[PDB]
Length: 148
Length: 144
Image (cartoon, rainbow over all chains, first blue to last red; front, side):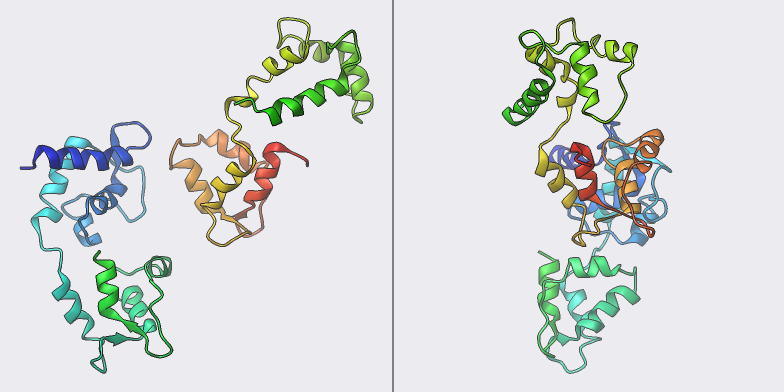
């Protein structure tokens, strides 16, 4: 069960996203409501037990606040979400020369071509400019920036 | 929120029409104002209908009160320009049609389908689907 403090924090997030004054969040937004609570849910997590519709699709369903409370507790708060240790050894698959350096094109390609594929717009928004001559991107610096 | 800029702007608009008995806009004053305005919109019922929006005798103080509807939004010059700027990443050529249509229709204080038609009939656009924000800002206050 959640604490009173957790319930009110989840509510403070909820009262931003029911923006039309309805007391109800549109179902599409629930993934990003979870992101606003500091959990990092995959779109595969989001469409299953969290009950989300298609990606970027509005109108289909809405969620009351009390309905949202088990949809925080039993979902991303009931699973592994990955740590630093995951990302470092997943990136080391693409570390050809062992120096902590990956090409910016290769890192963009992993984000856009593999997994739950990223838009170029998403990739550029998160890029902190850390590209040298052909010294390329320190991938550990990218992971620490994305996990702060 | 009726600013000194706005009321002085309204004061000259009153004063150009004026010249009638000590500071009152009347029927004749409006009729001969139209003569220098290039358009024969001087039809008697319509002209005298514009008096019904005040209790009587349109002096300058009454003229400001008549414009009470106008102030009910009316965020100042560069604030509307700055508001639109947040939704442009690409720096003039401005807001992509799909994003703007979503922004008004399904985001914030939602536009009705009639409101969307009311705007698309007077919005500036290209042939691909982009919408000029600065030209919309100019249309709000008008200079052509």
